[PDB]
Length: 28
Ligand SMILES: [Zn+2]
Image (cartoon, rainbow, N blue to C red):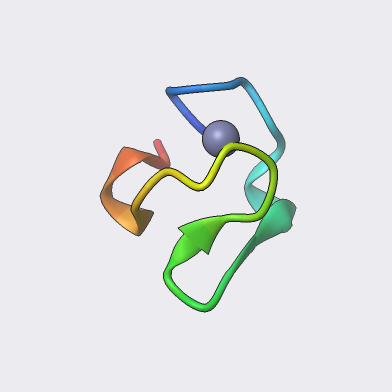
């Protein structure tokens, strides 16, 4: 999940959470 917004990890692309724009690092 994205620690910043809760989005499912499946939603990360291009180095960013595609929901909230968090840097990749924020996925857990
Ligand atoms: Zn996010």
